[PDB]
Image (tube, coloured by chain):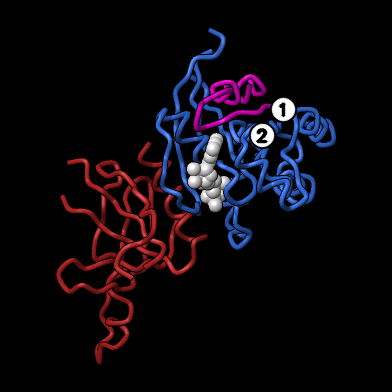
Chain colours: A blue, B red
Amino acid sequence: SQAIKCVVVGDVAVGKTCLLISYTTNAFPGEYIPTVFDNYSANVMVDSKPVNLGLWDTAGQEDYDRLRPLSYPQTDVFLICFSLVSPASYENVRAKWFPEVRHHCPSTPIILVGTKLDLRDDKDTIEKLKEKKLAPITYPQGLALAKEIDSVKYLECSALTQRGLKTVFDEAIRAVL
Amino acid sequence: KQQGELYMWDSIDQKWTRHFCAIADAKLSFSDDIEQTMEEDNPLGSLCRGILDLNTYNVVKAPQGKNQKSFVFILEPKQDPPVEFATDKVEELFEWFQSIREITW
Ligand SMILES: Nc1nc2c(ncn2[C@@H]2O[C@H](COP(=O)(O)OP(=O)(O)OP(O)(O)=S)[C@@H](O)[C@H]2O)c(=O)[nH]1
Ligand SMILES: [Mg+2]
């Protein structure tokens, strides 16, 4: 089956846990429960290539900044996440997450992921966003952040609707074998 | 390899108590109580009171703790009772949990 280790990092509340849980259980958690750390599994095929996918959920809170890197040894592929409806989390990719990730794992493929794709064109979100003189992140914007960090790929998706979810994991694995 | 102090939880006395614990092959040993072997007007105290067989257990981490500890994991028997452990610091919970989880998978 070939073990593949995958770690998911990114800002508080960008929807890392939902991504993992919705993909692994096709059920969307309504929770909301801040994460310390957590482990998950999937056995998948890909591309004819049976795999065993270890999934590591990390904490977004900086308080757990000492914990987080404990997950990084042996990692094969990273998912750096930001919410398409939260330019703070997008900026933090270049500020914190990609530097931290590269500090520890200089060589492992990264996969930039824009989350909450379903709120991108949401009336009620663009309203509150634009009340902070802000704007949802756009496909070309995400694409450009990918370039700066030389991520193997940029992918947008919604865990709640599942648009593009399978695809995030199916190129996370392809980035490995 | 994996070794260190853990709190252990007594279902009967409803208290947590400190034990030096360690792992070898796939057996976890816990010592006697450290505070109580140290109050002892005697010296007694065993490093190995007893031994759990990790092969017959699964590790489970409590999402939000248990019994007024924040960082607790549980050895839930596959066959025996649960053994409930706890650390002071989350970085211990992590290390401990993974050792055993790698052993139980
Ligand atoms: N509309 C929509 N909401 C989402 C989506 N993914 C997550 N959310 C919401 O965002 C909230 C936080 O999600 P969560 O997955 O826990 O973020 P997180 O980054 O993992 O949270 P943390 O543990 O690091 S603090 C949840 O209430 C969830 O309902 C999504 O794809 N679409
Ligand atoms: Mg989380």
Residue B5: x, y in percent?
A: 40, 68
Tell me what residue is drawn at x 65 percent, y 28 percent: A156
Q: Main secondary structure of the magenta part?
A: loop
Tell me what residue is drawn at x 44 percent, y 32 percent: A41
- Please tell me in which quadrant of the rendered image residue A147 appears: top right
Q: Is residue B69 above or below residue A70?
A: below
Q: Is mark 2 within 8 Å of ligand 1?
A: no
Residue A155 on the magenta segment: yes
Residue A9 on the magenta segment: no
Label located before the other in sequence (1 or 2): 2
In the image, A161 versus A64, the foreground residue is A161
Looking at the rendered structure, the kind of residue marked 2 is Gly
Tag shown at residue A154: 1
Q: Is residue A31 above or below residue B71?
A: above
Query: Does the residue at mark 1 contact the one at mark 2 (Cβ under 8 Å)?
Result: yes
Residue A157: x, y in percent?
A: 60, 28
Q: Chain of mark 2?
A: A
Tell me what residue is drawn at x 57 percent, y 48 percent: A13
* Residue segment shown in magenta: A152-177
Residue A80: x, y in percent?
A: 67, 39
Secondary structure found at label 2? strand
Tag shown at residue A112: none
Quadrant of the snapshot with the C terminus of chain A: top right
How far is disc 1 from disc 2 in space, using C-alphas?
8 Å
- Please tell me in which quadrant of the rendered image residue B70 appears: bottom left
Query: Which mark's residue is nearer the viewer, 1 or 2?
Result: 2
